[PDB]
RNA sequence: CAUCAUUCUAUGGUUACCCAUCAUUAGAGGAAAUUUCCAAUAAACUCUGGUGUAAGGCUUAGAGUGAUGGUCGAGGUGCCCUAUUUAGGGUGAGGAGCCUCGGUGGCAGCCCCACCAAAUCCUCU
RNA sequence: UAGUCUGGCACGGUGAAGAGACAUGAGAGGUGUAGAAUAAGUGGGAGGCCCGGGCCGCCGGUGAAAUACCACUACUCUGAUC
RNA sequence: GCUCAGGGAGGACAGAAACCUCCCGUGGAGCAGAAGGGCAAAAGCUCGCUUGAUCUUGAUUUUCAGUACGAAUACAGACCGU
């Protein structure tokens, strides 16, 4: 947590890999690369009941705990890669996505570039569930 | 029981001269700790750098994988 | 049974009755240089297999509990063994049995 | 353990070069100790006897009312009776000066129990122990602590500091502060294996010298 | 649980407190005098008919439900 | 009548060493939630001795006197749950270890009342 | 008990790199209150110092214990090797 | 020092059975256990103090070969308890 970085105005970047599935939300800051990571706290790490692991509140608590951990190391700004469950599963990002991004837009982190890395298959394997689907 | 982030050297990422904006960002790496070397586990990192961050005033829908 | 940790009994060296300190006897560790254990290993070593009997037909379940009497008067400090009859349960000055007391 | 030097024990008259001071000097000595335990009963205590008058200069008080009154009147002693010892040892808490004042006391024989009251062993459990013996010898018995052995104790720094010699006496009894010191503290040996590495021989004050 | 046991007649110290410290206030109501000085509400009314005819209080409002007194005026 | 603090004494006290504490070794023991009881059950930690490490009165008996014919005041002291989290909502039992007469406010300092913490935590619930 | 598996010793050698040790020669290096003063720790000691002359002392005071000038070992990080 | 099992007669609550007295009470109870023997100012019951369940030579009895072991009986020398 001591870098020879110029301290005033010139920003120090990481990229936060916000992976919002429908049953958990992962706010995970890494470097510019992704190879070395900085902070990772999830929805389920904060709120201790399984149904509100994916709540937008649980994802907010995470991104607040991410951001204040990220200011100790002095990574000022964040690039963003938003991600849904993806593959053959759902491409619409989870409910915790926006609240978690807003949480480190309210914390004090500068926002770099936002994109989707939702692992979109060109052409997929077979999907879990039947011919007749997931009945209820 | 100990901080792993205590022992992170902070290295600069240079873009080749064909691009305008030189400095890309900052890459924390664990120091040489006996066998495994700082430069060793650093010489294959991809950087997904947008053109707008790399060339001065141009399109911001093009990215460039640059490896150390 | 139950034996008290104190016993005003005969001390051989003192030649009188003096108060002793009662403690349960245990075995010592077998010396590796006792003549029998030396003879054993010389015989046991090499080929021939087990040379002397291994007792297996274990019949009795309790010991003759032995007391290690120790003279309290600090010039003497002489000791002797005091073997008592076989008993399963055994304690040193546990809880004196009382009379006119309710068994609840 | 054995130092074994007795070879050509002179050249300690090279004193005018090692010294350029003026005053009362004490030719002190420190010994190299290795692999010793501070906390446990690793015991390095008692006294190592010198025969050859080292002459330690400290504040001495001797308690009695005997021949040792008029025997020590030829020493110029402050000889004191029992009815001045109460005000010496009453004020031990409030009065901010060091109350004992004099860095030696005494328990006698014929006065065997000098004082075993609350005003007595209050003194033998703060330092400066009333240790020196004055049985019925009655020929010196005062100056024979300032003329007798040098002392050593154990503490939790693994080291030792002791005063062996002096400026005042000639350089023939100061090698008898080596001869009758190192002949003992070699033979003074328990299983603190080969404790004597080497002997950092000193003047009072000056440049390094080596014997062993 | 907690049982407040007030004085029906004045302890010597409490009348020494009531005939000293009560006119030093800005209000004299028979419920504050009762609450504060550990005396009774009816007794605190009986105290202030006597201190009325001493001329050391000030009768501002008197009603059956609520009588109010205050300190004697500055001048 | 009880307990502590004080000095004065007493043929008294082991000084390479006494005692309160810190610790480990040597034994005895529960209320309650849970009902309808029965006899259990099963801790937490206290009491007395050894030994050992800082200061320095011991623990014995007599007398004078600190604070009470009756004392301390007499009050803070936990866990549990919650996106009212400098706050709100619970209500069980029984065990040892600590600031001092607080500061501020309101009719001020007394009587009251408010409001901000000191070290509390272990177990059968 | 054959064989089998396993560890050690010998045959059994060269060269580098890393690490944990350890001897050699060093710097930084300790803060119950309080004394004006980050009191490692003992043997000091009212005694020194330099260009005829001054300072650190001593006491006052915290504590079981206070420097100038002689040395050593306790013990925490760095750091060089025939 | 006491007398037990059991019975009779009484006595608030109290009944077939709690407790309290008086009377009868040869053992009809009890003495750790199997059974037999023994036992009433005791060998039982309740208290008091205790460690003779200690130390030591021999002899003897029981089984018996008249050998061991176990168990036992009379002494003797100590030291002890009551």
Image (cartoon, coloured by chain):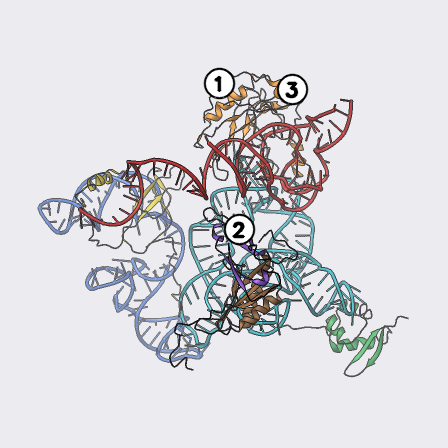
Chain colours: A brown, B purple, C yellow, D orange, E green, F cyan, G red, H blue
Q: Position of residue C42 (x, y in %)?
A: 21, 39
| Res H58 quadrant in image | top left
Q: Which residue is mark 1?
A: D6
* C35, above or below C88, in the image: above
* F84, above or below C27, in the image: below
Where the N terminus of chain D falls, by quadrant?
top left
Q: Secondary structure at mark 1?
A: loop
Q: Position of residue G61 (x, y in %)?
A: 70, 41
What's the CA distance linking mark 2 and mark 1?
59 Å
Chain that bears disc 3:
D
Q: In the rendered structure, are the residues bearing label 3 and label 2 in contact, judged by CB atoms less than 8 Å apart?
A: no
Discs 2/1, front: 2
Horizontally, is D60 left or right of E60 in the view?
left
Q: Which residue is mark 2?
A: B7
Q: Position of residue F14 (x, y in %)?
A: 53, 36
Depth check, front residue: F28 or C44: C44
Discs 3/2, front: 2
Mark yes or no: residue D163 visible.
yes
Q: Secondary structure at mark 2?
A: helix
Q: In the rendered structure, are the residues bearing label 2 and label 1 in contact, judged by CB atoms less than 8 Å apart?
A: no
């Amino acid at each position: 947590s001591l870098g020879p970085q110029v301290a005033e105005g010139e920003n120090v970047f990481g990229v936060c890999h916000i992976f919002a599935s429908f049953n958990d939300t992962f706010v995970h800051v890494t470097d510019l690369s992704g190879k070395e990571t900085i902070c990772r706290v999830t929805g389920g790490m904060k709120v201790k009941a399984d149904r509100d692991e994916s709540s937008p509140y649980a994802a907010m608590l995470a991104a607040q705990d991410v951001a204040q951990r990220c200011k100790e190391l002095g990574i000022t700004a964040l690039h963003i890669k938003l991600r849904a469950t993806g593959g053959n599963r759902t491409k619409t990002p989870g409910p915790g996505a926006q609240s978690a991004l807003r949480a480190l837009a309210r914390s004090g982190m500068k926002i770099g570039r936002i994109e989707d890395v939702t692992p979109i298959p060109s052409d997929s394997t077979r999907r879990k569930g039947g011919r007749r689907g997931r009945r209820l | 029981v100990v901080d792993p982030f205590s022992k992170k050297d902070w290295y600069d990422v240079k873009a080749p001269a064909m691009f305008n904006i030189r400095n890309i960002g900052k890459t924390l790496v664990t120091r040489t700790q006996g066998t495994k070397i700082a430069s060793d586990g650093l010489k294959g990192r991809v950087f997904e750098v947008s053109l707008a961050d790399l060339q001065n005033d141009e399109v911001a829908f093009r990215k460039f994988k640059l490896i150390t | 049974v139950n034996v008290p940790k104190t016993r005003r009994t005969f001390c051989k060296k003192c030649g009188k009755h003096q108060p002793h300190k009662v403690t349960q006897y245990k075995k010592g560790k077998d010396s590796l240089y006792a003549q029998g254990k030396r003879r054993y290993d010389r015989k046991q070593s090499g080929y021939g297999g087990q040379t002397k009997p291994i007792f297996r037909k274990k019949a009795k379940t309790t010991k003759k509990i032995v007391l290690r009497l120790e003279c309290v008067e600090p010039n003497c400090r002489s000791k002797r063994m005091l073997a008592i009859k076989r008993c399963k349960h055994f304690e040193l000055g546990g809880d004196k049995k009382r009379k006119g007391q309710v068994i609840q | 353990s054995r130092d074994t030097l007795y070879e050509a024990v002179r050249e300690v008259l090279h004193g005018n070069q090692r010294k350029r001071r003026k005053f009362l000097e004490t030719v002190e000595l420190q010994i190299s100790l290795k692999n010793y335990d501070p906390q446990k009963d690793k015991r390095f205590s008692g006294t190592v006897r010198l025969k050859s008058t080292p002459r330690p200069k400290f504040s001495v008080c001797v308690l009695g009312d005997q021949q040792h009154c008029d025997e020590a009147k030829a020493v110029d002693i402050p000889h004191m009776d029992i009815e001045a010892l109460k005000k010496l040892n009453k004020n031990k808490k409030l009065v901010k000066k060091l109350a004992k004042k004099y860095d030696a006391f005494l328990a006698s024989e014929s006065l065997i129990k000098q004082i075993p009251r609350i005003l007595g062993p209050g003194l033998n459990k703060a330092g400066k122990f009333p240790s020196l013996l004055t049985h019925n010898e009655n020929m010196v018995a005062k100056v024979d602590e300032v003329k007798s052995t040098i002392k050593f104790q154990m503490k939790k720094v693994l080291c030792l500091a002791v005063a062996v010699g002096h400026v005042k006496m000639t350089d023939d009894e100061l090698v008898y502060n080596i001869h009758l010191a190192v002949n003992f503290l070699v033979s003074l040996l328990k299983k603190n294996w080969q404790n004597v590495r080497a002997l950092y021989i000193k003047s009072t004050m000056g440049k390094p010298q080596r014997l062993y | 649980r907690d049982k407040l046991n007030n004085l029906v007649l004045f302890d010597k110290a409490t009348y020494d407190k009531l005939c000293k410290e009560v006119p030093n206030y800005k209000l004299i109501t028979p419920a504050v005098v009762s609450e504060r000085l550990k005396i009774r509400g009816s007794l605190a009314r009986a105290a202030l008919q006597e201190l009325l005819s001493k001329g050391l209080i000030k009768l501002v409002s008197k009603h059956r439900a609520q009588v109010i007194y205050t300190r004697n005026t500055k001048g």
